[PDB]
Length: 73
Length: 153
Image (cartoon, rainbow over all chains, first blue to last red; front, side, top):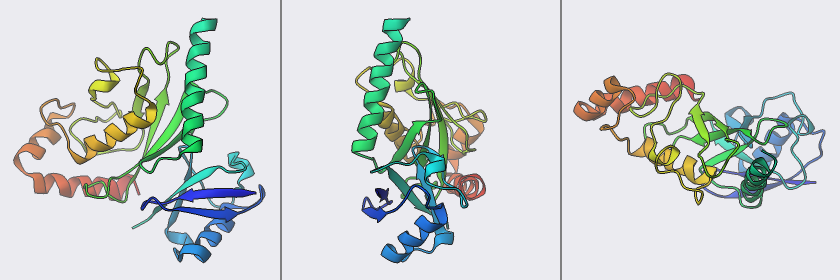
């Protein structure tokens, strides 16, 4: 399935994933495409902070859902 | 009852559906769980402001007669601002007397972002912070950044 990630600039990234993929795995995919380190990434889905060790399925992220990406500083 | 809350539920659903089809850059928001009347949202510290970098969490509580009365919106994250207080209450017109059904939760969060960029020190929930904004803007921006580093990152 595909999910999308919106960034601060407005750009949307597109990612291929499964429901069992962990938030870490998704941060890794983002690093591949954009070069942002996982330790700098904060992901958010419909108001909720996504934490490491939990799955997309645990947060009920679905086909074509859109997360938001922020950076730590 | 039935019909009142059906219309509200139809409307909340339509706003959620619109957020999924066309995600906005200024916020993200959605139901906490089962209950469509209780959402959470995030706001990003606007880039130009002293809140840049921070991620601010809010709760959204839709009344049963929504959208004819406004939602209840409150910060859960600590924020240093003249128009937002210790309990996360927000002094904003469009959440009270200026509320209109034409507004959405997304537009409200946008206006709240404007409030972080351009505070209104004449209608202050926190007079102390308001006086600092009025008579030492540099101190104000410093403390705002300090609180954003401390609570919202």
